[PDB]
Amino acid sequence: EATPDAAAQTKLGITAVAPDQAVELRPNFGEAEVQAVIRAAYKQIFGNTYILEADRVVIAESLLRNGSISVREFVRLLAKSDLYRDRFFRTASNNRFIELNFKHFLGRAPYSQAEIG
Amino acid sequence: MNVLTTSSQRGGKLFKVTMTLSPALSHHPWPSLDTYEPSQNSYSVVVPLDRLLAEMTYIKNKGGRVLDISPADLEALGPPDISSVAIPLKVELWAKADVSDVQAAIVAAYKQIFGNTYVLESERLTSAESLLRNGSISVREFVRLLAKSELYKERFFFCTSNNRFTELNFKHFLGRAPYNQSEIAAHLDRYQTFGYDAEIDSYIDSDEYIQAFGENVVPYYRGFKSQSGQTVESFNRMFKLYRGDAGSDTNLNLQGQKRRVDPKNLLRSGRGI
Ligand SMILES: *[C@H](C)[C@H]1/C(=C/c2[nH]c(/C=C3N=C(/C=C4\NC(=O)C(CC)=C4C)C(C)=C\3CCC(=O)O)c(CCC(=O)O)c2C)NC(=O)[C@@H]1C
Ligand SMILES: *[C@H](C)[C@H]1/C(=C/c2[nH]c(/C=C3N=C(/C=C4\NC(=O)C(CC)=C4C)C(C)=C\3CCC(=O)O)c(CCC(=O)O)c2C)NC(=O)[C@@H]1C
Ligand SMILES: *[C@H](C)[C@H]1/C(=C/c2[nH]c(/C=C3N=C(/C=C4\NC(=O)C(CC)=C4C)C(C)=C\3CCC(=O)O)c(CCC(=O)O)c2C)NC(=O)[C@@H]1C
């Protein structure tokens, strides 16, 4: 009984995310390069939910251009957003919130009940 | 680097932190040994006061080490205004100077020679002042006396390094900042054999001194305006050596005497030795 390599991935539809491409902001970044990190960050950090024009956070991503803040600081600004609160936390229970924060902030899920506590 | 906000949305004094980055602290998502981006050997972050303790411990627990911390409010301040030093002003001590004119020179000399640094009534030199105003001493010669004086040595030369003392000297005796690593090296060697007096003598004696404010002109700030044979970077170094009006050269302040001009910056303008 034979399986193509990457059969395990294609079942479970983890094919896209299994090995996952990293996006890095680089020095003297171009205008298109930054746009791509933003695009990525909003997809991971936010949930794969839809960010409409109104939703976007102008001030945080302006600082990301001109290197005032790093991407780690960009992520922190995104995470403390009416928008992040409105989705995620305000409707969720603390168990569902903490489990969501693991994932968006770090790809893993929570390893144990202690971590939740 | 520039900081764009003094305070966080929640009230909190931001503080710029500068570290030497380490592979652990940030690394490329690449195969092979982790490397920090070369351009960010010295990384800077602005953190609120609350996260400052945690931020710094983490940096240090990795191989990071902290280059310096500075309040964001002092940072993200205008480069000093050059208004007063763009055109120095200049003082000439005529022969047959009346009482007031001599006084003005004296004041001006103490200002330039000592930096903003204050000279108390007891510190002030009657003898040297005496000589000026019955003739006998040139403004140039008075200036030599001041740099010979202990007052000068105690502030500039006895606290800081000879490396620092040289540029400190340059600025006081010549408006210019130092150009090139060579000047710093020459002065140091002069000092080792000839001693302190000969070094002081070599700035007043130098033709650059003579060409500008040669005799009977109180020294003024030549730097901040374009001078012959001056490296372009020297102009930038003048902004480091001269911080605002009401900023001084002070042994008094914490770790008072340090180097305004980094050694590396000097190397850029010229190397050879
Ligand atoms: C339009 C023809 C019909 C329609 C669609 C519809 N979809 C939503 C909301 C979502 N749709 C998706 C779907 C996707 N995410 C993806 O990445 C992909 C492609 C890989 C799809 C197709 C998602 C995730 C959402 C949620 C968006 C969010 O997170 O905010 C709606 C809106 C429902 C809502 O209340 O948000 C609608 C209307 N529905 C119709 O009636 C049309 C027939
Ligand atoms: C080899 C010919 C010479 C040599 C190299 C050498 N390099 C290091 C350490 C580092 N080298 C770099 C270089 C880069 N990082 C980058 O990201 C890039 C490209 C974008 C370069 C070119 C960096 C940043 C480091 C320091 C941190 C790191 O390890 O990534 C060493 C070791 C220094 C140490 O003590 O760690 C060495 C030996 N040095 C030699 O001996 C050769 C002459
Ligand atoms: C008095 C209200 C408070 C105080 C003051 C204080 N200042 C110093 C030392 C200096 N302060 C200045 C001030 C200025 N320099 C300028 O040129 C101007 C505007 C043109 C000002 C106002 C300077 C130059 C110095 C440094 C030189 C020197 O100290 O001789 C001190 C002395 C510091 C020391 O430790 O010796 C003090 C005490 N401090 C207080 O206690 C009051 C709250």
Image (cartoon, coloured by chain):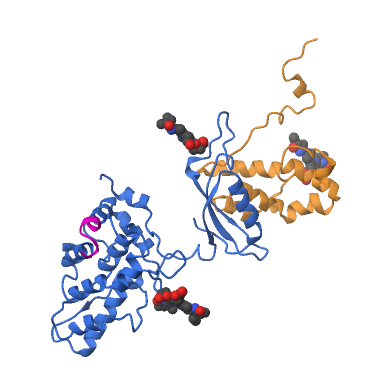
Chain colours: A orange, B blue
Name the residue located 80 percent from the left edge and 44 percent from the top edge: A115
Side (left or right) of A106 relative to B74: right
| Segment tinted magenta in the rendering | B190-197
Name the residue furthest bottom: B99
Q: Position of residue B225 (x, y in %)?
A: 28, 64
| A110 shown above or below B53 | above
Name the residue located 76 percent from the left edge and 45 percent from the top edge: A101
Name the residue located 36 percent from the left edge and 74 percent from the top edge: B116
Side (left or right) of B85 relative to A87: left
The answer to whether residue A48 is seen in the rendering is: no
The answer to whether residue B9 is seen in the rendering is: yes
Q: Position of residue B129 (x, y in %)?
A: 23, 82
Side (left or right) of B119 relative to A76: left
What secondary structure prevails in the magenta region?
helix
Q: Quadrant of ligand 3?
A: bottom left
Where is residue B205, by image quadrant? bottom left
Where is residue A111, by image quadrant? top right
| B183 shown above or below B196 | above
| B257 shown above or below B92 | above
Q: Position of residue A116 (x, y in %)?
A: 82, 45
Side (left or right) of B265 relative to A55: left
In the foreground, B57 or B14: B57
Residue B193 within the magenta-colored segment of the rendering? yes
Quarter occupied by the C terminus of chain B: top left
In the foreground, B191 or B6: B191
In the foreground, A72 or B170: B170
| B184 shown above or below B110 | above
